[PDB]
Amino acid sequence: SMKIDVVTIFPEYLQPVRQSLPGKAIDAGLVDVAVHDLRRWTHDVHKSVDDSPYGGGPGMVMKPTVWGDALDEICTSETLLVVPTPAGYPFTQETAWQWSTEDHLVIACGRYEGIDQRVADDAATRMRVREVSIGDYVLNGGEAAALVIIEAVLRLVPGVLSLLEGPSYTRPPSWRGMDVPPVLLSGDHAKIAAWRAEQSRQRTIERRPDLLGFDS
Amino acid sequence: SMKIDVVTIFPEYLQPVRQSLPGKAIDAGLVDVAVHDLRRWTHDVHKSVDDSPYGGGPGMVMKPTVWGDALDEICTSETLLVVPTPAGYPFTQETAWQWSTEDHLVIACGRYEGIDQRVADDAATRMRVREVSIGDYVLNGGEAAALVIIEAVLRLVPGVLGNASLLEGPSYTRPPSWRGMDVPPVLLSGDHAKIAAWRAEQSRQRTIERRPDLL
Ligand SMILES: COC(=O)c1ccnc(N)c1
Ligand SMILES: COC(=O)c1ccnc(N)c1
Image (cartoon, rainbow over all chains, first blue to last red; front, side, top):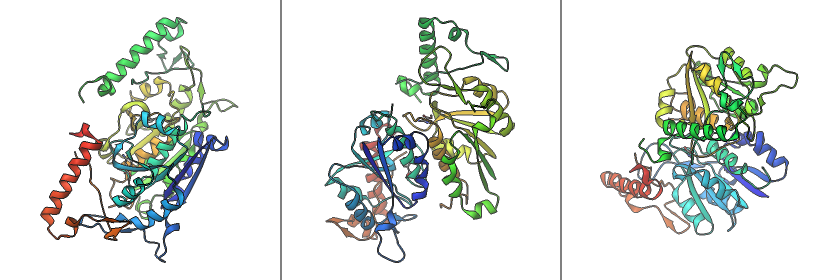
């Protein structure tokens, strides 16, 4: 069993984790996902979680005090603290495999212009911390990234179940005048394997030449 | 100004995103996000959306006849059809900027084994189609990728979500000392040219450490 805790100021945005495979993994008892409202750990009546950045700049930074209290309660020395951020190390398939064997993930979701760096620095004195980016784009908050990470990891957990995959087809064999590639209907496993390997390598050079060690 | 239609067998997955739209943007008619259950376009009593792959192999492939009907109803010639797939072209910040001025996005959410390729190929003969990946990992379905794409795009449309090279370096706020860690004194110095130079060096170091590909 894995435990995943997600900490966020928008707990309602994490509801989709109840759908499809994360939902089915939860129902199978393979994982427990708990979502926590960061404002639970505030003490002012304003429940303030942010303030202006030292040194200037646009926007607001999440305060370390509130985060520290939340993580103190939720984390242990065995926790893997995951902090989604566009400035993170890349989260990849390899990362997903690695984290799939973890006992406890805590995902700290930032909003505004990010979380005071001392939160991660303080946590790293007690536990393993991983600041990660899920791709080359910016979001308003870490919540959607948390959903991506949870899905990519949970589908790899024992008991739940390079190159680009080429096109796939199913019935009927002809549709709107478009035919399924005849080799796929031929029953020749060697020819199908070869055609699929070729399609995979062809799609990869077109869409992801970087995966084969080429420019762009 | 932008309409987004999402087609999925898990429509509830997209509902917090709809709720997260500020009323002011909806009232101003800046944005409309509609979610459609793909099973609306199934043909049989069992509401079948997938079938075994031609050529053999594991998993299931989503049916072209079902998807074809769904897109026929939902798309027009002006539609940008977005198909999240781990086998796609990379979705990047540049892509998000490009798509932020579109009138109509339709996002087709499929299982990772894929939608029958004839669906995208047929659609591409009468509209613009973009098969895209949001990163180097596999999900079970495209729904979480759809959420990422919707958020990355809509936050670039003025007034829609409520928000106003090298990696950004660390940020700090009050208090100036916390658990034995002080905010870097340069940030309190009132020397704003020096602060900018310090931030540039922090950005350089962080980029070398975390994303050497960017240099
Ligand atoms: C606020 O979080 C983000 O913007 C984010 C998080 C993780 N990966 C990204 N590419 C963006
Ligand atoms: C099923 O969809 C995916 O697995 C997917 C979609 C978009 N980008 C990815 N990296 C994966």
